[PDB]
Amino acid sequence: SPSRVLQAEELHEKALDPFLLQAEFFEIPMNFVDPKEYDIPGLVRKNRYKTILPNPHSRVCLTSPDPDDPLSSYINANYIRGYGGEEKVYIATQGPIVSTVADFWRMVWQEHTPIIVMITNIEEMNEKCTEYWPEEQVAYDGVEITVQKVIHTEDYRLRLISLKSGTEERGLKHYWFTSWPDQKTPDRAPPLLHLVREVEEAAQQEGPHCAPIIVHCSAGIGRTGCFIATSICCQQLRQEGVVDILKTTCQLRQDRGGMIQTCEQYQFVHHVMSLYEKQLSH
């Protein structure tokens, strides 16, 4: 796997060299999936983008309501390895569309997902994501979703949610980040880093072997990949005192084609990690 281990000084300088960054970035294979892989009638209606498909080896398959129906069992989502290759730390998925809102909640229930991270600005709720949570309460497929509390913070809005299906009840935290920048300049890094830290602590609070954290945006690759890469690299920096964004990005691409879609995104991850290193070093 490609690797570029950055110590502090090289990290700071690397984040500020857009020519080297793009040279490096555009040699990472996208690892997109051949559409022939999901040539099933009606399956196209379940995808936002025809070219952005879940790699089959890591695809999340839905086991209800009909596991013998390839359409019913399909969602555009992949399991994503975390730091050190830990399996199923995240699920990367597309923002639900009207026809997949119920599927999304089926995934949440099936995977026991305790945390969702939504990276969509309020302005983008017309294009990039269908509002899939209730004002108070809604049910899809025997799982009742109840919003118990909304907590507005500067860098995100956190919904505390209860999921009930049958006799059993589970908690869920929905983190909605609304500060995704147009220009991915270093001044815009702190809120993303803060989100990353908040979510990683929430995850530790779930105890051993936390169920997959769902992360989405519109396609489930760009901003989603930035968030996951940053999360992984924060653990790497703390443990190893270095970051290897190149290796991490390559690992993510193995799990889901296109993770970190643009060079601006790739650079932004470097800005965030440079920021975090500075914070740690002081």
Image (tube, grey):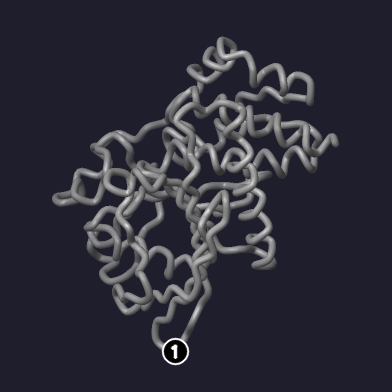
Residue 54 in sight = no
* Residue drawn at point x = 75 percent, y = 38 percent: 237
User: In percent of the image, x 66 and y 45: which residue is there?
Assistant: 83
Which quadrant: the C terminus? top right
In the rendered view, would you say 71 is above or below 264? below
Mark 1 — residue? 167
Q: Indicate the position of residue 78 as horizontal and vertical percent values.
A: 43, 49
- Residue ranking furthest to the left: 41
Camera-side residue of 257 and 8: 8
- Where on the picture, by quarter, is residue 164? bottom left
Find numbered disc 1 in the image and state the secondary structure of the residue it sits on.
loop
**Residue located farthest toward the top when viewing the structure as drawn:** 19
Q: Nearer the viewer, residue 192 or 22?
A: 192
Q: Position of residue 147 (x, y in %)?
A: 44, 73
Q: Nearer the viewer, residue 227 or 127?
A: 127
Q: Residues within 10 Å of mark 1 (few under 14, many from 20)?
A: few
